[PDB]
Image (cartoon, coloured by chain):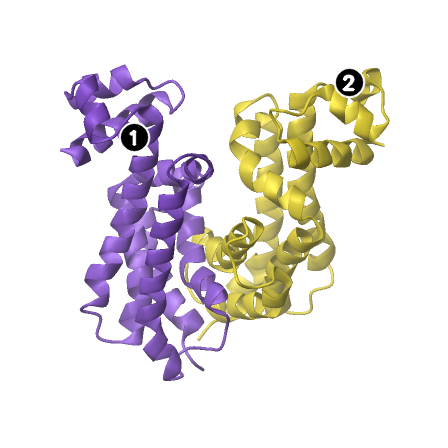
Chain colours: A purple, B yellow
Amino acid sequence: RKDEILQAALACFSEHGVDATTIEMIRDRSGASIGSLYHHFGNKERIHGELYLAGIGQYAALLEAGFARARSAEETVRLLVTSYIDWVVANPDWARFILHSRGRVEAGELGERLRADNQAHFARIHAALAGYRAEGLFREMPDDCFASVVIGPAHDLARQWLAGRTRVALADCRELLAQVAWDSVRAA
Amino acid sequence: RKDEILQAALACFSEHGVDATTIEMIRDRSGASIGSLYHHFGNKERIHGELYLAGIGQYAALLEAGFARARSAEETVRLLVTSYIDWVVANPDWARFILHSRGRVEAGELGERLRADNQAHFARIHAALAGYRAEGLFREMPDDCFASVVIGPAHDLARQWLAGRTRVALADCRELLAQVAWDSVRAA
């Protein structure tokens, strides 16, 4: 179970830091042999990038599931926000890891896959929003601006919260951030 | 001129990366002797933290100047956003450096000063907003939520823009992000 191996790696990385974690620590936490870790993935660096890609992959999967049942532009926008906040609250160590690891992954051998994954993710979101945008349901702005207005507050609060720099529980701001995202981008 | 030395360090860091920059490279770019670099600041690591603190200090100074002449809650909110966007557009290498260096600075010997600076900055912003908040000019939310709604989109777009991941010029989204910040936090 590759998922089991990635969660072991995450636990090691969170406890000891990335650089101080060895492949030995991952086999001992995961119960998989070193041969097995290589068969499923590869060395520590490959496992590190796969952990990254799986984490962003989980957010994209939430969106895919949700776009299918969203009943309105409002729900579609809210989904981008609640999916991120809920995923972070459920996976705080994984969120921390993702927020600190992109540069490292893009620099290495999984850089191409990261680009392709990112492209697929953006494309699905763009397709989900496009009919509503055509219907004039949103205030006029560039697609990149829309993206940052919808998710920027949640990204920013999550970053502060994870670093222990807030006086609020992230889950306690879920409804507010969803509501503000919709109110920020909806037509006047 | 300490400012001159910090700008030299920034140029070195941006060109060669932090780890590959030596104190020798900083003296050669800055025209200051190694004795002088130590007299004004210290070694590469101290210079690195001073560069960080000066960068956040410049944003706080913009706010201080602006709070004095803002004629309304709307202008006060807009100021938090235009100051950040303008500073990033004027100082893209410095912005990149700040966005990637906090962990390193907080971990080291300038950690106490970083905490005290951060505390002073937050306190000034809290004082600037408090009368408007008392007047019911804003939608109800926790202070930390307000902070992330106002600046999160700008932080997020700046991050993407600096990394070459946007199809927009950051300066071309300045008015939109200021307007959205005000619209996002103002009372209904």
Which secondary structure lies at badge 2? helix
Can residue A93 be seen by looking at this rendering?
no
Q: Residues within 10 Å of mark 2 (few under 14, many from 20)?
A: some
| Residue A15 x, y percent position in the rendering | 32, 23
- Looking at the image, the residue that sits furthest to the bottom is A135
Q: Is residue A122 above or below residue A1?
A: below
| Circle 2 residue | B38
Relative to B19, B90 lies left or right:
right
The quadrant holding residue A185 is bottom left
Chain under callout 2 = B
Q: Is residue B158 left or right of residue A185?
A: right
In front: B16, or B110?
A: B16
**Identity of the amino acid at label 2?**
Tyr
Residue A121 at x, y percent in the picture:
33, 57
Vertical order, A91 against B187 (above or below) = above
**Numbered disc total:** 2
**Horizontal and vertical percent position of residue B44:** 68, 22
Q: Looking at the rendered structure, which numbered label has been put on residue A47?
A: 1
Q: Secondary structure at mark 1?
A: helix
Q: Nearer the viewer, residue A127 or A181?
A: A127
**Residue at point 56%, 70% (across, down):** B176
Q: Residues within 10 Å of mark 1 (few under 14, many from 20)?
A: many
> Foreground mark, 1 or 2?
1
- In depth, the one of B19 and B141 nearer the eye is B19
Question: Does residue A28 appear left or right of residue A59 in this picture?
Answer: left
Q: Are the residues under badges 1 and 2 in a single subunit?
A: no
Residue A13, how many percent across, how many down? Answer: 33, 26
Amino acid type for the residue under numbered disc 1: Ile
